[PDB]
């Protein structure tokens, strides 16, 4: 279960999926600020998550921190270093007192945004299917490892 | 645990999403045996999950149990009874001893299958978008509540 190789096998994530995520890097990068604004504004709309963004109003760091994570989904090198880093990300949220429910909530926001980029840029059905399948795997892997930080 | 109303607000799940899911019920009904076979075969194909299907071998009651859950996604009405039932579903996996990682894996299988039904049956880009968005919300809400069952 615990190694990256094992996790990839369970999700049937292969080098083809990694190549497809790399092929989406330019679109993700083009759209990174739109993603960051929509992500940040959605959180500002829920009082419970809005709390965590009060100090950030002045510090002005957290929009960039989550923007950078989004870009990393497409950066390649999905290896044991990548999983270790996700475990760290998960624990950061546990440490500040964020309920895991809001991680699931946030991940829905990213998922809808990214699938809309795919729908809007890939008219060919099988190109679209393959890119959607790769993105759903990486988002689900991210959510899986982060969720496990609340248990472990 | 949160109320259905609060969960819907966090996921921006509206009466329109509930109506779209209800409208997918006949489509679900005509794909349910294909879903049930693919879901059960995927679990047989990982040794860790296949261990939990040993007792089920002869009559495959669990294949039906999982099929029935899939069709229930498309009931078109969702209130506190639906959240309570998801807690019961999560708890059933906790009590048999299944690591929650495999619930995330299985939800990716169902997600990919269901989004292919949407792509394969809805040529109109906006009809597709709206149905995909409703499906991703209800799957993410199921995953969210089931995950919560593993936290004291
Ligand atoms: C898709 C879900 C999420 C992902 C992938 C994510 C990603 C990250 C990353 C990469 C970091 C930097 C952690 C580190 O390396 O130290 C971080 C920190 C942080 N995130 Fe998130 N995040 C998510 C959801 C949320 C939500 C919903 C909130 C609520 C407002 C939030 C608030 C925070 C805060 C407050 C920190 C800094 C913790 C500290 O002060 O040490 N995150 N997040
Ligand atoms: C999308 C993820 C899954 C969903 C939505 C789901 C759904 C369900 C439902 C609705 C039940 C009946 C619960 C009840 O009313 O008592 C159940 C039971 C069960 N499921 Fe799943 N399931 C999922 C993943 C899995 C996985 C990955 C396995 C691994 C083999 C599994 C094995 C079982 C077993 C063994 C039971 C019976 C537990 C008992 O003895 O009561 N399920 N599931």
Image: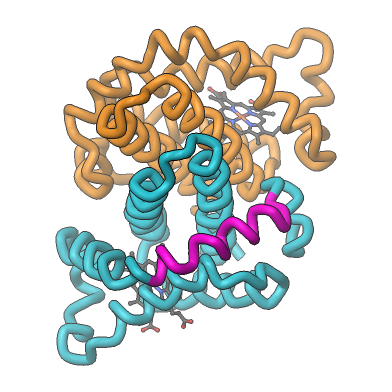
Chain colours: A cyan, B orange
Q: Position of residue A90 (x, y in %)?
A: 50, 70
B141 to A67, vertically: above or below: above
Looking at the rendering, in which quadrant would you find the C terminus of chain A?
Answer: bottom right
Q: Position of residue B68 (x, y in %)?
A: 52, 15
Residue B20's image quarter? Answer: top left
Instruction: Write the residue at 41% across / 65% down.
Output: A28
Q: Is residue A11 left or right of residue A142?
A: right
**Residue A87, magenta (yes or no):** no
Farthest-out residue, front: A124
Farthest-out residue, bottom: A59
Q: Is residue B16 visible?
A: yes
Query: Depth check: A133 or B19 in front?
Result: A133
- The residue range painted magenta reads A13-29
Instruction: Write the residue at 74% across / 13% down.
Output: B60
Q: Which image quadrant shows ligand 1?
A: bottom left
Instruction: Write the residue at 29% across / 86% down.
Output: A61
Q: Is residue B65 left or right of residue A109?
A: right
Q: Is residue A101 visible?
A: no
Q: Position of residue A63 (x, y in %)?
A: 29, 77
Instruction: Write the residue at 27% across / 27% down.
Output: B127
**Residue A28, magenta (yes or no):** yes
Q: Position of residue A25 (x, y in %)?
A: 49, 67
Query: Depth check: A100 or A125 in front?
Result: A125
């Amino acid at each position: 279960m615990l190694t990256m190789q094992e996790i990839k096998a369970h999700y049937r994530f292969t080098d083809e999926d990694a190549e497809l995520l790399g092929s989406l890097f330019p679109l993700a990068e083009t759209n990174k600020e739109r993603l960051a604004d929509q992500f940040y504004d959605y959180l500002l709309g829920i009082p419970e998550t809005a709390e965590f963004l009060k100090e950030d109003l002045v510090l002005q760091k957290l929009k960039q921190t989550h923007q950078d994570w989004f870009v990393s989904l497409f950066a390649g090198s999905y290896d044991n270093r990548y999983i270790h880093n996700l475990q760290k990300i998960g624990h950061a949220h546990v440490r500040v007192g964020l309920n895991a429910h809001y991680v699931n909530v946030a991940m829905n926001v990213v998922r809808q945004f990214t699938l809309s980029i795919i729908q809007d840029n890939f008219p060919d059905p099988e190109e679209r299917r393959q890119r959607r399948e790769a993105v759903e795997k990486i988002l689900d892997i991210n959510l899986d490892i982060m969720s496990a930080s609340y248990r472990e």
